[PDB]
Image: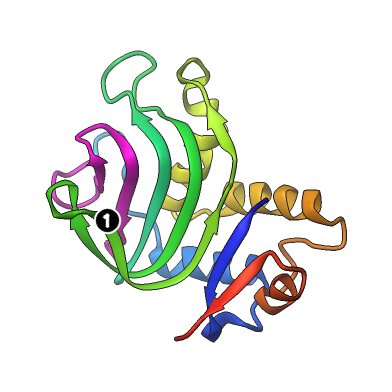
Amino acid sequence: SISISYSTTYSGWTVADYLADWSAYFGDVNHRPGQVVDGSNTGGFNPGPFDGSQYALKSTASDAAFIAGGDLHYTLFSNPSHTAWGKLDSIALGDTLTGGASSGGYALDSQEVSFSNLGLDSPIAQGRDGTVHKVVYGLMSGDSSALQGQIDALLKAVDPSLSINSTFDQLAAAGVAHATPA
């Protein structure tokens, strides 16, 4: 089942309001054809360079950052080009990305919320139509809609009474979420 960890700071937030707010603060790194700049808006894979158990990206607007976890791949210039695919198990959100492939992987200095056991799996042949591509590219480009839609389905599969409009504390009461100290 989907497992959620959250800083007690967001106890009374709905998942939808947290993710819309987080995405607004993160913004859009503008990783688009003709706007990709080395050391500015690429993020990185661990172990990488183009695959791994983690993809991490820091905001160009703020200290906000996300880490995508599972078994992830980027096609780069190979057909179908510029596609992120594979297994997405987890999304961690907060501030101050640290680490890299030779430093033990990626972590957040200030992790606010993580979603685990997402059970998402997109094959390479689906290209940018894949759910994994839509979720992670959305976070990159300041649109958490695709992530919100997946979390909503996963919560309703636990109990039809739960949704993206549940507070973190309501999800703790239903045994889905666990508070961490701020």
- Judge whether 31 appears above or below 105 on screen: above
Identity of the residue drawn at 53% across and 27% down: 122
Classify 20 as above or below 140: below
| Any part of residue 30 in sight | no
Q: Is residue 169 visible?
A: yes
Q: Quadrant of residue 42?
A: top left
Describe residue 40's horizontal placement relative to residue 128 as left or right. left
Residue 144 among those drawn in magenta: no
Q: Is residue 132 left or right of residue 156?
A: left
Magenta highlight range: 35-61
Residue in the image at 55% along x and 31% along y: 121
Give the residue at x 22% y 36%: 48
- Establish if 40 lies above or below 83: below
Image point (61%, 58%), residue name: 3
Amino acid type of the residue tagged 1 in the rendering: Tyr
Q: Nearer the viewer, residue 61 or 123?
A: 123
On the image, the x and y values in percent for residue 178 come to: 60, 73
Residue 2: % across, % down:
64, 53
Q: Which residue is label 1 attached to? A: 106
44 falls in the magenta region: yes
